[PDB]
Image (cartoon, coloured by chain):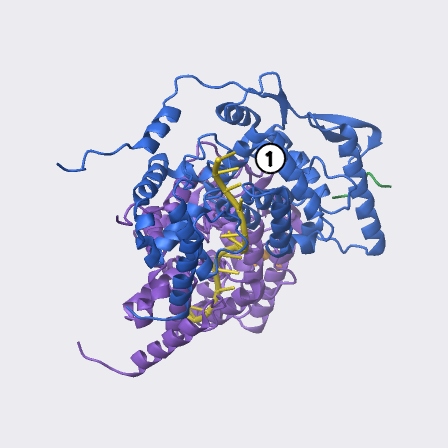
Chain colours: A green, B orange, C purple, D blue, E yellow
Amino acid sequence: DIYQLIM
Amino acid sequence: DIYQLIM
Amino acid sequence: MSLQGIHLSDLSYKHAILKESQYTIKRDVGTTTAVTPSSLQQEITLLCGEILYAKHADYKYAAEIGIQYISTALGSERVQQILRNSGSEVQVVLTRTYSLGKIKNNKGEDLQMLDIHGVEKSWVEEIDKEARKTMATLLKESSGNIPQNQRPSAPDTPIILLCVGALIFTKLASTIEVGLETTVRRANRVLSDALKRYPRMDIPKIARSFYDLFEQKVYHRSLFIEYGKALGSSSTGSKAESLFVNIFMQAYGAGQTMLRWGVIARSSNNIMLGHVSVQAELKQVTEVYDLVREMGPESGLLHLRQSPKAGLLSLANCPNFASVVLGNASGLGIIGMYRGRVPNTELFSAAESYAKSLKESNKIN
Amino acid sequence: MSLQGIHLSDLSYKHAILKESQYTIKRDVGTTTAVTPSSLQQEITLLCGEILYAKHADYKYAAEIGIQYISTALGSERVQQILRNSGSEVQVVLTRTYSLGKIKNNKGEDLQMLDIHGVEKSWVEEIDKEARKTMATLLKESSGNIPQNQRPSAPDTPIILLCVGALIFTKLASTIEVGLETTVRRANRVLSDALKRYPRMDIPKIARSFYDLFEQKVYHRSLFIEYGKALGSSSTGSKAESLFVNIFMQAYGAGQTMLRWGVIARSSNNIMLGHVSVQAELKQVTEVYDLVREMGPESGLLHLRQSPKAGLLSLANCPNFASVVLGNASGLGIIGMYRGRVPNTELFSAAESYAKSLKESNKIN
RNA sequence: CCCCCCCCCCCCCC
């Protein structure tokens, strides 16, 4: 679940 | 009748 | 023989470096902002008036509604042009009226509500409904006691909102706390007639909204300035518009109080200006003032526009001149709560003593 | 009958020799460099923010990412023109967005990442992965506690990276150790809001990366300078951009501190300037300052650009004037740890004694 | 040969 962070 | 005020 | 060729002129060279650039910067390439067609000017005035006469849960986009009124005043395409010339690649999105739903108005048509890009429709709907409930309560309590100038549809409500905006604008070189306190204090007096017409406009929250908008969208500052320039250039106007131009002109030299206080120190004949430490720096001081003269009228708007070129006008590399200037300001009582640092305490004390002696005594020339 | 016709004007002649050349020099003919099209500014901004909020084992290409942001702000074709006008035949290469693979983002599309020439894709993958892991851990610690200003996607993160780069740029006439120490020391203060927002940006490693980049790719110095020129000419900007321009002006007279200190020694009225040994050299000193005036505003950038023409601005052939200038600076206490050589020790001592005596006493003119 | 130090800015009142 690491590549869908909002940033 | 709140939306019929003249304003 | 003579020490005459020993001269540098570095600040003029720095300004020549900055001014003479043949490449323009590109910022905000994929961002968008909202404008309103001038046809909707009436429908934005009402909005600017509904923020004023009711106590609202949230004031997030009050500054945006003021900017929308500015957009109607100047024109949408003109606002595109202003933003483009400000150096930002923001793409304008146009405001659109939409039918609220089954709701019917007094004229028999559907109730049309404004749709502003970046401003969620829930906020506009809740402001509208809250103001309508407030007017219903006021009419129920008092019948026939509502004049025109106590209604949201009064033509100067956008100008009152933008007067609070101009108050917060004057303190854009200060911090948020000092700016908010100054805005509330000066709005209690300057906007006293407007506050008497609208006894429940939340000046602190509107001012915080305006500060937020000015920080987030720097280009809007330029838009604001254009409105002021477009307002002071009008042949006629209203008293609210004249008040707006007065506050806008009070915002002029923002972020450069040391230059004005140096002119004051010279005007007061402060003899500590004759100190050798100050004489060793008067050359660069005069060079900064010459830079001001070269930039011209736009030099005062440098810090308000938040121009990166601002900082050439800084007198921070003349600590003895700055100390004497601050001492002269303190002796006259001008300094107030100015937080600019004092490098040389001895010159500050001497200048303050001389300024106190000069102000207390009287002379005839 | 008179010694009036004895004169040489050798420094002006050398400048006219070097300047009036009909042949340009070609360098870097077979080489290539990377740029990013302005339309990818958002995509580069994120990357410039992901070097900031995580602790990375390797910071090799951070300066390259800052240059990529400069390229997006100026434009790829305009950056190619800049690098050509700097006198380099480097062939610009264009950044390409590539899909990572089977990995998908929150929007349901393929995760597109930047592909920069000369930067291994593995470095970009590891920077992005470490940043994502760090933010995942931070959100595991606290929920909903991350505002926009603490996120990598903040628009000013490239400007923060470039401000660390500009701090290392100010010390490009110094050594690597002094430059790194100065950059860390000054960044602890100047970039304090950024260091609060991003508590784990490794300023020493980013500064070493920028120093490296300015060593291998000298033409990028020119690019850097153009950014400053393009950034100080903008009507508006952010606070970080004003900070960048402030440091960029602080870099101006770099490599020529003896000229500034000689102007100081003239403004300090050091009596040892009147010593006959210095008097025999004021004519060539005046020729050096005349050369500065002839070169104009671009004379300050000569050492930053690493121009071969730099060194015509050297006062090293006037040892007694140099000794008196260094002594006057030492007496006033501004010499610091400057390592310039003092040829005449006696003139240095006398000048320093007079300057200390002048600074201690106070007089009114 | 040259070079070599230090340093964001802003901040009051109307």
Residue at left offset 50%, top offset 34%: D305
The residue lying furthest to the bottom in this view is C361
Q: Quadrant of the C terminus of chain D?
A: bottom left
**Which of the 4 image quadrants contains residue C155?**
bottom left
- Front one among C88 and C42: C88
Residue at left offset 28%, top offset 32%: D8
Residue at left offset 65%, top offset 48%: C120
- Give the structural element (helix, strand or loop) at label 1: helix
Relative height, residue D52 to residue C338 (above, below): above
Residue at left offset 52%, top offset 64%: C179
**Which of the 4 image quadrants contains residue D9?**
top left
- Front one among C339 and D358: D358
Q: Quadrant of the N terminus of chain D?
A: top left
User: Does the image show residue D107?
Assistant: yes
User: Does the image show residue C244?
Assistant: no
Q: Amino acid at mark 1?
A: Phe
Q: Which residue is mark 1?
A: D214
Residue C106, position as x, y percentages in the image: 56, 53
Residue D299, position as x, y percentages in the image: 41, 37
Relative height, residue C290 to residue C96 (above, below): below
Residue C161, position as x, y percentages in the image: 49, 59
